[PDB]
Length: 304
Image: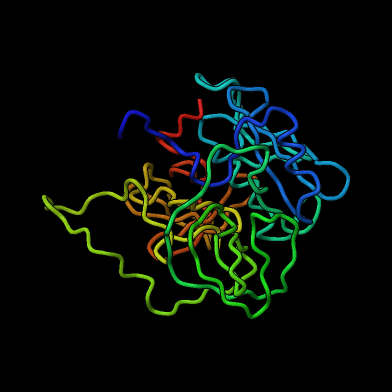
């Protein structure tokens, strides 16, 4: 708004252009599980992934681009990007960054058990200081880690939410006073009562139902990867009306009938592009080439 404006920075995991030691030093002797994404790779956009474990960090190579990465096609080179997106790493290939980091939601990762974005370190210029809240959560496992920025969780201990710095880790305080972040797929979501009330805000000049633009506030209305093993939901994927009509084959059975108009959510995302969605309460797998996929696509992304 003022003479400064912004974009992301204080959004979630992404890290800044780590010179060279930052991305390695900051991820070195870190927690038993940690990963980070710095900007220093080929293509139009930077894609890398360093993971800690025991002996130095493990930087991984990743590929990506602006075009839509729903399913792996056979194109040549995107107009804006440098070449076909598609992700890479350890003889692997996903489609989206958030889709990649979303590996611990199912079962461990390349190295260690359930990793997460590293603290800040590497000498940061920005410090968090927000007073956001929501309903509180309880720890379902013992406490233990390495990074001071995060907050170890002690079984049966109740933690109050204060902000969402990651897609798999929210910020909460411990019964000792210490502040930090707790895991999403390790605690139990608890809903007391004083969570969905807000102030008021009100309106001024309305008439019709607006579109889901901007993005809802973090909380019960929209929480990070809590039930999504693959599909992302940092602020809310594309939810409106199918862009193209794609019906199921006659020889099909448990297939989904997709038609431009209705609204479908991405329920269950496979590796080779074929994902399943919810349309008219029906759950089935459609080509998905007639719908606007989800992952890491933002209008004002400014990736390139």
